[PDB]
Amino acid sequence: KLANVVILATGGTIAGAGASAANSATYQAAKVGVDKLIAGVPELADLANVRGEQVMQIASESITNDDLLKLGKRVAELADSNDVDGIVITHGTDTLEETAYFLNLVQKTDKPIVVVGSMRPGTAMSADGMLNLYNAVAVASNKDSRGKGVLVTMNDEIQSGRDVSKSINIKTEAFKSAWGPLGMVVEGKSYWFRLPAKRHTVNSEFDIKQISSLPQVDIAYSYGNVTDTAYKALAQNGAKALIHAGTGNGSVSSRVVPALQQLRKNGTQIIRSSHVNQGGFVLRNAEQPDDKNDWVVAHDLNPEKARILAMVAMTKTQDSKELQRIFWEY
Amino acid sequence: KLANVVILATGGTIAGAGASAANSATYQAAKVGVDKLIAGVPELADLANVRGEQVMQIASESITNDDLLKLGKRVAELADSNDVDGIVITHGTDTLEETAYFLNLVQKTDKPIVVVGSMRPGTAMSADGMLNLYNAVAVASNKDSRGKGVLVTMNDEIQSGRDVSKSINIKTEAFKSAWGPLGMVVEGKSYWFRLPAKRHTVNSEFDIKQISSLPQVDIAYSYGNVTDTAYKALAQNGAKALIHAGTGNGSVSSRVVPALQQLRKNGTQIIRSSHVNQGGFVLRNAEQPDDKNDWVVAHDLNPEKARILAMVAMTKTQDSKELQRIFWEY
Amino acid sequence: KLANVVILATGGTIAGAGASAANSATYQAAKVGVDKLIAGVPELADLANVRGEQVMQIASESITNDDLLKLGKRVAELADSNDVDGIVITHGTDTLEETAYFLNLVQKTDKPIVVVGSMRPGTAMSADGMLNLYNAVAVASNKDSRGKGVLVTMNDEIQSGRDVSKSINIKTEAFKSAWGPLGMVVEGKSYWFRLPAKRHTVNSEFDIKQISSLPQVDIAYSYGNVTDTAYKALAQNGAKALIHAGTGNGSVSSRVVPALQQLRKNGTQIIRSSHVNQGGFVLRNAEQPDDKNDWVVAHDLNPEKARILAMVAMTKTQDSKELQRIFWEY
Amino acid sequence: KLANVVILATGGTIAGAGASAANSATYQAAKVGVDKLIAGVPELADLANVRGEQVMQIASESITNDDLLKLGKRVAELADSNDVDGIVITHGTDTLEETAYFLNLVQKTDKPIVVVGSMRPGTAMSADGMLNLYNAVAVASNKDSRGKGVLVTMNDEIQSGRDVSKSINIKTEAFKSAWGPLGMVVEGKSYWFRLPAKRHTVNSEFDIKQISSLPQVDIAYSYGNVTDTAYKALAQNGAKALIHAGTGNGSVSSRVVPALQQLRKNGTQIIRSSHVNQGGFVLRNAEQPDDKNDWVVAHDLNPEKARILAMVAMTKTQDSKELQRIFWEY
Ligand SMILES: *[C@](*)(C=O)C[C@H](N)C(=O)O
Ligand SMILES: *[C@](*)(C=O)C[C@H](N)C(=O)O
Ligand SMILES: *[C@](*)(C=O)C[C@H](N)C(=O)O
Ligand SMILES: *[C@](*)(C=O)C[C@H](N)C(=O)O
């Protein structure tokens, strides 16, 4: 009859509370349990047979790699159950773009996986959480959502977990993608206008079942007068790969090039990303001789997205050439 | 008759060269002298009397604090002269947003200061540098441009140097501002639609003539599983202030808070900015108890922008409350 | 103590109702009275002394010129009262951009005039109306809002009534301006980043007290294979001016030029606007010889905005040169 | 070896000329022949074997239905030939979005069809036409471009001809799509990030080979105080379908509804589109009782886009329900 959708709660602002109804930016995250969030949206029963499960209760800015894994493996078990048609995960918006992309790479299933959260706490007036959840379930319950990879439903849109990013603060249209939304969801119906072109879920070469722990990967910011300090400190403390968030097209200061070459020889992967994330992408060999130095470009992925792909990829390969190929297909 | 405008060349892609006409992104920067540039745009003579001056020949990704000081002082000199009505500066786009903001804060003059660059080298077909420069001189020669603060002229727009940022890679519309452009420049004419509302140039409490050196300020990136490693390494190497490029609304991981509190007690200013730079701003006391920890909020300025203001501001005060007032007025 | 703000209700979706809480796009407009909308936001009393007045109850798509006048004159009376500090008007979003601009041109007062509405009806889950109203009052009560012209507060932003336009359907970030927002409002506080540069309110040469009725002005759309039919039919039925919503830069088909020249000679003002409204503006004499034909360009104003300015301007002048000047200053 | 690509010239600004190099917006279109164009881009020879063919020399604002048919049939001819791998068409930008969508609907071939223009004439400094054409041929020669539908290559992007629209005037980034670009083209290479999800070319139920003429379809604009004048005049002059460019979600004024009901009974199809074209879409039965009145909703297509689909669709059916299914699939 109706689809069986499971909601995995992880905390976030969607489960947070404020001092008054006028508090739409000042609140305490992860205060409400999954059962209460379901009860707050009575109409949910009209969309699917839904049951909630509290996986964790955290503010997403304080998420760890073990949390991601615990979440990834749990999702995998649910997707393996013939009694589960769709999966919705409520997650704080600060690192939601990171978790959504992670799942897109390691969940080998065509069942819909939808990640959702809200910019305003549930206690604020005109809170965006109720409709976001409703739309999340509506999409997870839809047959047309299968095989589209991980999705995020906020601001009446259906966004790809791959490249959607929290780009605007405070406002409910916080999440944007340089390549646009895949569609929209209005009054329960899903409307598609685009399809993903990058490898995901079922057609991914990675699998959360084979992963026991993630390699350490960190990010260093680049700007005027930057020195190699942050890069070396991160590498010396364990990083197996470093995401260079350079100016413009992954540009690197001449004062930092040496440390990067040295680090590369030492076994540390160097991936060039940038802090120009509204559009475009980093081109190989353009700003730096990547072939000569044996570095890797993150294509269009912003720093935090790059880190996620790098971590997953390195559980299978440590070959810079294979890494580049992966950054060009995922 | 015609206004007297001086062009201060600093390098960049606008002065760059590519291997072929088909090379629009792969090139070598700072290869052309200011004389060659001016020459390439004969029509300039119609707008005003122009003379070039090569201050330096660098790629902006490799700019240093001494280069800023050197450029800022030279600008203050030409502005004081009565034989100068407007000033145009060619600068690489990678850190143009940083130099543009710096000058907006320290040049105590109402004469037009216009910063311009090009996304494509002059050797590329359909290069954008010729028209950008022409519009730069057109704007710097216009009386209506006085008292507007530092301006940047690219993509037929008149952008404010304060908040214009390189947001899109590769494409010519690379520079955007969350609050929009101030106006446009078409066929030599300037059209205004908005006015700046933040303190700048003449009404700035800072003066390049009173600044001999700039305090060291660095930036740490925040993301899932981030540790206090980068923050401490940076402080250990001299940083007098640290820009925290947090997720969401300047959010800080619970794993890093203790290190940030210790660093503050030690005298390191802590400024919360973010990597959500398309819109909105970081609110004081929302995600963290800034009052209690004596931290500072960067308002709407992205990481590299906040670093510029922090530096300048710290040549005059080290009082966090005064620092906060400064971040709310400039 | 507190400011006295008056809320003039005109109907709209903000006062509309849906069949269920899941109905966020399908609803019946203008069903709720001003008193109920106030009672729905208890926190309002914390911002100012507020009183409501139901001016009319309509769906804004069915608004008439007499409605605008009735609204304009009413606002004028309130602004004349020493007992009124701010004015907030709830208005359907479909033609809100039209009414907000109208008021910006004819209300000779520096007191804050804020127009607001909502994309979702008050009965939908996560309805945006409550916070929008709250923010509308917060802004109207602020002293810093004076002298900024008419403002619109939705999606946590402070937009200029001049050029903000409903650009996106369904979503709460529906209103955008090619020149960006003037600021934002969060948890009661107003944050400014830009200032208007065009003439408005107190510095306008128009006055709602001198206007008894508006001249008829209509709009004709332009596209491939368009004929002069719509243009002539509108003129023959009373239009004193016609807004040409052309392709690109106010371009006109060669098959329509004649009718336009003929109409001009007959006394009908011809104003070239366009259906390219995300940015840029229409340039005089670029696509058509406006000087020779004696036509007028709408600069950056979209068709419906152009119609509003044209109507107001023609109550003072019928000189095409003065009309052009007006389109370049307002 | 190299692919065989044919360039069909139709005119436009790309083939235009300005009075001076400083003229980027003021110019005269369709002055250059296809041979002169190809010649101006020597590098083309490296991408493939190209031959030009001047089909017509017009300004796209003056295009007619016979020009569309003539262009569509010529395209179907070249596609059938085995001596043609890809097809490039230079077209004025003003109505390029219309021709691009038309071809996407009627060309039953998987060979790449790329439409390109230029915002600046070739006589302007920093003209954009040279690189745009180069990228057009680069994309039309690429095997990965097959089965993607009609494409448009400007601003280093690969846009879908279905929903790409000229949204910004003057600037080179004029063309945008609510659902984002499909990919980008840099230094001869194509990078894909999204795939089309709507029916096109090979899977289209329409075929230019079976279309001798197109039914007349016109567009009426809606705004404050609009009357049924334009709607009726248009129907009286032959319109078989009327595109209603309403405010908001295709909203219709209560003053116009009766005329629209009478026109429908008389056999005129009524299609509700809107002038809110940055995002979202018009929902069936939301603002008006479409089922009851037997009207049709344009979904996300702007007015000029909806007109193209209505025309094409009406060469096969006049059943409103089938028309609606068509507007939801293409
Ligand atoms: C609250 C606002 O969206 C987000 C929190 N910091 C979180 O991500 O838990
Ligand atoms: C070339 C593209 O603008 C940019 C530079 N690398 C520079 O900043 O010099
Ligand atoms: C409802 C949605 O915002 C808008 C109505 N049609 C109105 O403007 O009254
Ligand atoms: C010139 C700017 O692209 C455009 C044209 N008027 C045309 O469509 O021919």
Image (cartoon, coloured by chain):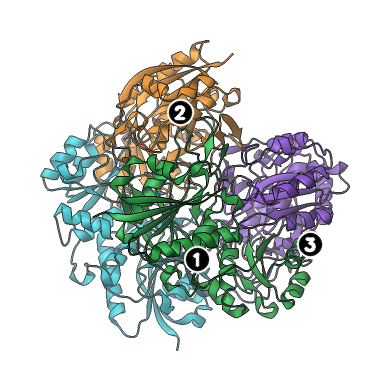
Chain colours: A green, B purple, C orange, D cyan
> Residue drawn 63% across and 58% down?
B225
Give the letter of the chain under mark 2: C
Q: Work out which quarter of the rendered image holds the N terminus of chain C and state it.
A: top right
Secondary structure at badge 1 equals helix
Q: Quadrant holding ligand 4?
A: bottom left
Q: Can you give x and y, in whole percent of width and height, for residue B5 in the image?
A: 74, 49
Q: Which residue is mark 1?
A: D129
For the residues marked 3 and 1, what is the alpha-carbon distance in whole angstroms? 45 Å
Same-chain status of marks 3 and 2: no
Q: Is residue B313 above or below residue A268?
A: above
Q: Which residue is mark 3?
A: A229
User: Which image quarter: residue B123?
Assistant: bottom right
Q: Is residue D274 above or below residue A89?
A: above
Q: Can you give x and y, in whole percent of width and height, for residue C313 in the image?
A: 43, 28
Secondary structure at badge 3 equals helix
Q: Is residue A291 above or below residue D260?
A: below
Q: Which residue is outermost to the left?
A: D266
Any mark on residue C133, and which? 2
Q: Is residue B70 left or right of residue D163?
A: right
Give the letter of the chain under mark 3: A
- Inspect the image, locate mark 2, and give the three-letter code of the amino acid beneath it: Leu
